[PDB]
Length: 282
Ligand SMILES: Nc1nc2c(c(=O)[nH]1)N=C(COP(=O)(O)OP(=O)(O)O)CN2
Image (cartoon, rainbow, N blue to C red; front, side, top):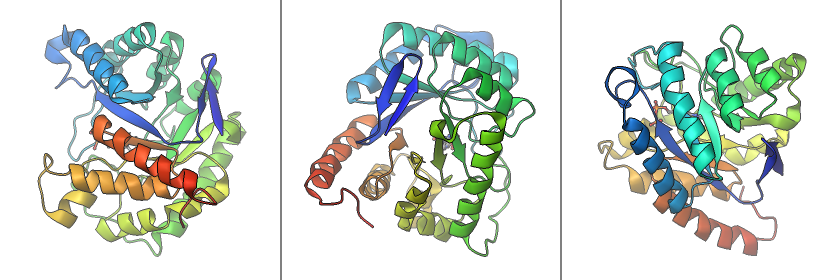
């Protein structure tokens, strides 16, 4: 499969590692945007050099009790980091925003994929994505990510994530975004408990019936932390196991913090799925 954006294509026959670059207020310092601009631009360079093919630049945190960020604060941080990267390097850039203004502006400075974890549900978001014309990632979420609320009860989580995708693709086709430009993502850790997350991981091979690209984000989440009982620094081995499981079943993009070791894992998976008659495990 192939994505086409900004005059270029992305070939999804092999898995891409998407590096994370979060440029929040509490990290892209002091007041209103520092010399943190060189750090951002240096961080991207190491990831690109670790083998990353997409960088996901985002200005909000979505962990529990995370503060709201305003459009000014997003536009000050995200857009100059997006522009600087696209000028300097030939990577693909996803913007992890939910605000319409930030979608319209990232488009103009060179971003390639809109990766809104809220799946364009904010007033005005869907049509900003639509006029942009770029690939959009749709993600399953239940409840609000930034709350301190325990997890939903699902009658069945696979069936519910799957109904959600059916609904969402239609919404998009009606806005005028062709099913050709969507990517789907089960939302690991968003409104799911430990079992719901591993049931969704165990059956990931099966969301391929949509014939859309699969994006997966599992790096250093609680699905590894609680299972192993380690802290956020101590989750690399468990985060690599989630990336290999997921790419063995054909996921197209793996969004990680630890780009060097994930890219290295993806290479062994490549080696393996290439010798494997139907190129996928199920
Ligand atoms: N497509 C996609 N985007 C995402 C996903 C994900 O699962 N899929 N997870 C996130 C987790 O956000 P959090 O604020 O917990 O932190 P992180 O940027 O360090 O991963 C944030 N953004």
